[PDB]
Structures are given as structure tokens and as C-alpha cells.
Length: 302
Length: 73
Length: 112
Ligand SMILES: [Zn+2]
Ligand SMILES: [Zn+2]
Ligand SMILES: [Zn+2]
Ligand SMILES: [Zn+2]
Ligand SMILES: [Zn+2]
Image 1 (cartoon, rainbow over the protein chains, first blue to last red):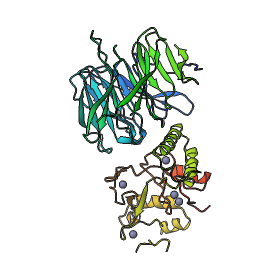
Image 2 (cartoon, each protein chain N blue to C red):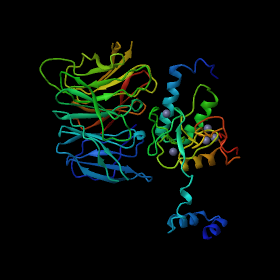
Image 3 (spheres, rainbow over the protein chains, first blue to last red):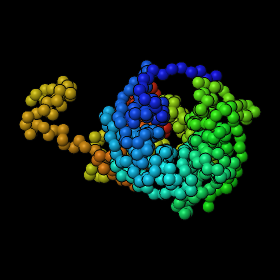
């Protein structure tokens, strides 16, 4: 039932991302010209341009937003082997702290949920995930890398757990994009035992054999279990019922090949009921659930 | 109409908190305020927001309950 | 004499304007006397510094408007019987709309 439209915006170079803030009034798009720019929807529904500035030497792939409670910051990664932050001063943005501790290309950057503070997770092609901290919301010019996680493989995408119930310990999902002839799990999950005060490997999905492009976590909204979508040759949705690391009851719920190609990106709604997936077939297919608790398509857009 | 055992559950509070956050996403501030009135009058366990109170410079204590005169000293 | 005459007519804007630009030391001191407040956190009951919006022991941002749940960095209204408040503009609109403390507590902050 989804109908399309066209957005009145003009760019020069190809852009690699789009990301709303928390309300849906500020997007942040990174262009192939190393130039990121921020739009701002107005009261009349139009989109204007507010800022733009070139980034570091590499090529930017990801730009993410932050919760409005902490101010207005964005984290962006590029092949410059560095991760950046940006704060509004009013509007001239300023660099605050370039988290440069990686010997490879930091593929992904993501922000931790609000309920625990200002953390951001990055891992590079070397296969080591880093977690950073801002233990003074006052000044953003000071960060600390507490935990380093060995992955014994590469990174493609990571995603946190939106769930904020006290029962659930913090969780993280690390992908891989290695097409080695051997077969190994390419998606793994880590937990955080407060007793050991460290991140421990919890569960891995052995059914994953091909390279993985993207991973996302469906928001909780008070549910009992968790919902996870993995980008592969086929879109797949897994649910992990809670039972050291907590044992997880894993069973598949969907497996979709209605693309005839390789899936690139996966996204979720605010509620966590509609999935939007994009692939090399040049179409965007949105999947929702039906009355029989069955996962089926709802619109194919191009 | 809930007796003060169901409302204490860790599950029955999560749904209210998550609905309130969803209302925040709507930017439906006044609807949330009305719902807060409703929840507060029907659930004694909920403690309202923690905010600032001002304090005197000589007594050192709060002024919240001569009008111009402080009630402390 | 001019400031007294101005205040007599309830023209506070221009009186304060004369105070601010007054070219003598003895006149540019009337609004610098006993006009600064001391702010506290209602969870920890300890003072906060003069250039911040967060709590050193609490860590809870103690400046949140009771209408929009956003950090208040400038003007902050405060009801005296509730110890609740928020943005200056938000609270006015809420109080025009209804007569309840927006945070939620049986209390009519103006008694209608
Ligand atoms: Zn006092
Ligand atoms: Zn405190
Ligand atoms: Zn406000
Ligand atoms: Zn109140
Ligand atoms: Zn009041």
C-alpha cells in the first residue's frame, strides 16, 4: 500500500547514506565528493540545505545521528582510518575528537542506546571492534576506548539492541563479508557480564555460510524476545528467546528470495513491524506480517 | 483499576514508559501531559520527574512548601 | 530621579535600559545586588556549578522541560509548590491550556 514520490533536492556526486535524527526533521547525507551536508525540513514540508563541509582524506560510507538529549552530534567513518564527531555551534560545525586508533578502514560506526550514556562502536577490516566513551557530557573533546573485541574475521556491519528493559544486558552483533571457500559463521553476538565486567561471546548463527552485508535489530517495544534481520543472498529474520552468557533459543521465522540478487541494506521501523530491504535488482521491497503470523511482502518500489 | 501488585511488575511499567517515548517521537507533548495526569492519578507508585529547586544563600535550605521573606530563617 | 519617575509609570524596560548604559559606577550597580540564585538537584540535594546543566553525583540532567522532555539551557520557570518547571514559553502555553502541573502531580500551580 506504499506509494512513492520525489524529494526536491539537488546533489552533484553520488551519496552513500541518509539518516534522520530522532524526530524526522534533520537528515545527513554523505556524498562521493567527501562532502557531507545536512538538510532541515521546514514547517511547509520543504527541504532546505543548512550546511556542508569536506571530510578527511578517505571516502565516507556512514553518517549517523545522536539522541537530542545529548546535544546534536554525528559520527562518520571513512577510509582515512578515523572516526569523527561534529557539534552545532549557533551554524558552523566543529571537529571535537577524531577517534583515530585503527590500522584499517573503519567500515561502520553506530551509537549506543540512550539509557547507558554516550558510547559509539566501530570496527575496521582488521577485525577488531572498539567501544568508546564520553564520561562527561559537558566536553566532547575527551573519549576512552575501554573494550577491544577480537573477531577472527572481518567486519561488514554492526547493530546494538534498542531494548532498554533492565533484564537485558547490553548486546552487539558483528557481521562479516569474507567469501573464503571455507564455511564458518559470519554473524556473531556478544553480551556483557557485569560480574566479569567484560564482553563475552554469547551465540553465533551457524546457518550463516555466505558473506553478510548488513545486520539490524528490531526495536523491542515491550516484547519478550528479540528480532534480528540479516542481509545475505536472501533476507532472513531470526528471533532469539532468552532462556556467563545467557543461553538463547534460536529459530528462523522467514527466508526471502524475492530479489534474485544480493541484499545490501536492511532497516526497521520505530515500532519494529515493517522491514525495508534494498538489493542489486534495483528495487526496494517492504515486508510486513499478516494475521497468520506470516512474513510476506507489502510493496515493491523502484 | 489495578491493585498495587500488578502495577509493580517490571513488565507493566515498560509498556507505559515505551508508549510515553513513542508519544515523544510523535511530538505530541500535550497528549503525553494528559496521559501523565491520568497515570499519576491512577498509579501511586509512579514518581514524577526530578527537576531543580532553588536554595537560599543564608539558610541554605529549600524554599518550596512574609511572602517576600524566606521561611527558613 | 529619572529612574524613580520611570518606575513610577511601570516602564521597567526603559528603566533597566538606563541602568545598563548608565555612565556612572553608582548607578550601574542596582541590578547586580542580590539577583543571583543558587540552584539545586532534587534527587541529590546538592548544589551544581554556575555553567552547567548536569549533576556531579546524580549524573541525571536536572534541566528537563516538563512539556517537551528536552534539555533547558536558558530560561527556566519554577513553580514553588511543586518544584516542577521547564521552558518559559512551553509552560505558559500549558497553563493557558489547563491548570495542572505538566509533570503530573495533584497540584494546581495557580489555583485557577
Ligand atoms: Zn534560606
Ligand atoms: Zn542529582
Ligand atoms: Zn520545553
Ligand atoms: Zn507539580
Ligand atoms: Zn505547582
